[PDB]
Image (tube, rainbow over all chains, first blue to last red; front, side, top):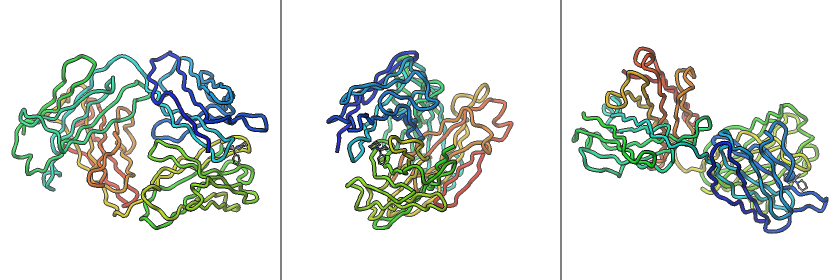
Length: 216
Length: 215
Ligand SMILES: c1ccc(C2(N3CCCCC3)CCCCC2)cc1
């Protein structure tokens, strides 16, 4: 089995910039037919890997010219000239020379840009959830950047953590931001027993929170 | 166009077997090899093996040999993978791909295989209105909370599909083996509450559709 190593695991870049994803083989993948079967796949999130480069150098039909691959028997490089937004996804190198056919680990192309403070939204438990017996306080921190951005849930001033499940949407390809969802789930029982709910947002854009709250 | 219709997410208890297929339309199903690849948790990629639809020539990765069985239906243009002895490690996304002697071509959409000893439990869709967040007078953010549904697949949609912009559907997290999703559509003040915003949720494994709204 031939090992494929893809460096870097994660490559952050800004727009119009250049990117270089390396992939190396544990051993030559130059086939005896005199050909090297190394492929480059770009998998966008919520999608399947699509083909960009076949046989090191060649580009697939309809793939933009900005992507160019090259390499020498053991070291390959996928190259991108002026990263665009739609270039987000995981990049994969593949070897169909020695069997079994191996895939390189993959590489993350998130896109660097201007910091954006999240549009924060808080939602109390909807009516049916109470009638039914549970309570879920939701908070949507949309369109932000960079990714590291903390959210602390505070009940009547006191910080709270257990019962909270956060979810991150992938970096939008049209604007290059993220959206998160924090849901403070707590039994109606422990909910009616309180007044204010604070969804606080710490982040690295402007070093100062954005606090949303409601009181029942 | 090489339209590979690989399809159907489905869950199966351990020990059981499953048979997934790929429909090849647009071309001569007999001229290209069909390959099988395993995308393990949207991350790792592994090769299973191939099948060539004119003679039945096939081959496998020694690691998938004990559980994989590849076959073709030449008359209906379909290739099938039979996964058996299903332990948790089998739950993953399986792609079907077309390959010329030299290279891969068109991959299929993808198949999700949840290997689970658990039951199918529909989603509880609770609608979300503000009254406490970034005011409703310029551009407001509404939400839909889909919680406590199994298995993993549910698609959240908005306004019969008549609101595709401004929607942020976050992935799902699993609480005690249930999945909780939440999406949000940031709409103009003019729309909600003046107009109807209807949240359309669907969950195959339970035949569950529920179209909601709020106050
Ligand atoms: C059957 C047909 C083609 C192959 C591939 N390869 C073609 C060149 C020679 C070595 C094997 C590698 C896997 C993807 C398709 C290309 C494998 C098996």
